[PDB]
Image 1 (cartoon, rainbow, N blue to C red):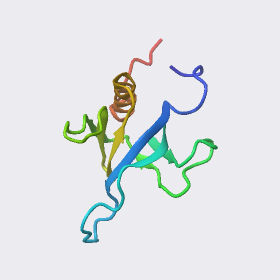
Image 2 (image 1 turned 45 degrees about the vertical axis):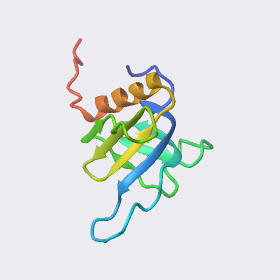
Image 3 (image 1 turned 135 degrees about the vertical axis):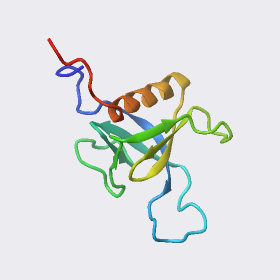
Image 4 (image 1 turned 120 degrees about the horizontal axis):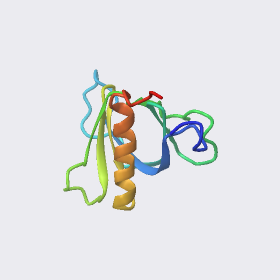
Length: 125
């Protein structure tokens, strides 16, 4: 699916990004911030978040990009009042992602899981 779908991002849409931790050499007592709502865009193998949908062409503003090339998605536990939420863990850091409609959620999980996974698809012919 190349040279067709407009844009340069596999998928895009508003989602709640809740990181588990960013630092390692720091002893903190509790998460730094709760569920954050920022436009999340998937371009290639990196996740570019945005506090607003004013402009995508440009990179993030304050939140650094996260690599998903080797991440691990898993339907977040079914305990959080938040429904249709998938948990993603990148070799660099870990975070969460919520959705609106189940159908929509599944879409993301797939799209991403497809990017991270080996791109050894049939590119012959």
